[PDB]
Length: 109
RNA sequence: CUGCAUGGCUGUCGUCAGCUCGUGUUGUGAAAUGUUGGGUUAAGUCCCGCAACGAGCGCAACCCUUAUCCUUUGUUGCCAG
Image (cartoon, rainbow, N blue to C red; front, top):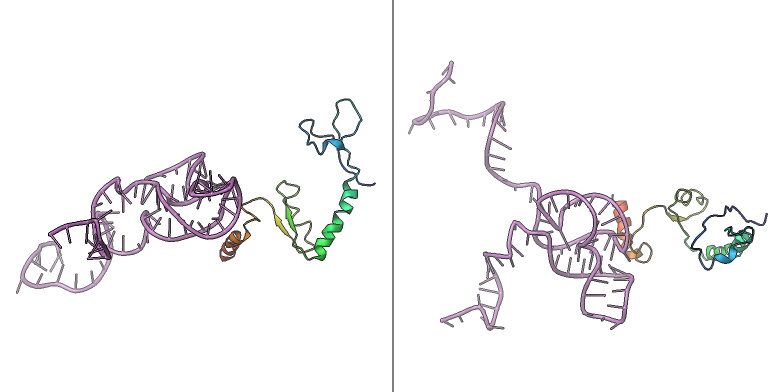
């Protein structure tokens, strides 16, 4: 009820040194993650996303996997938001004033 | 009188597929990246994709002629009817 979510446990090798402490003691040599902080850690981050929305910040969403690539353009369409669903460029965001010539190209075609 | 005094004008490596530029990245930096890779070609040509996205000179097309046809003008040329 504290959220918490789905576990199998999946991946048995090469764990990230900052994610290893989320493993819990159930069975000999068995990998399984504890998720009892998912929404408790989101409730404090969504407070600063509220501060960026208060500052009228432009929000960008990204996904390429089949569960996310369709959702970034449909599941948040109750506000004004921007997305990337499949294809990327060199300097996609860090060279935006060059990338604008491809938006002039898009609209000209 | 002479192209280390010149402007200009044409050869040749070279009709070869090369040489550069705006912004971004990379290194202390000259610079490198882009022009490489993977297919394809007559070709830095076209396609695919990537830290690149687009450009300038070459490139290529338009241009012109030629193999077959249809149609307009025919002498002192031509001669099918």
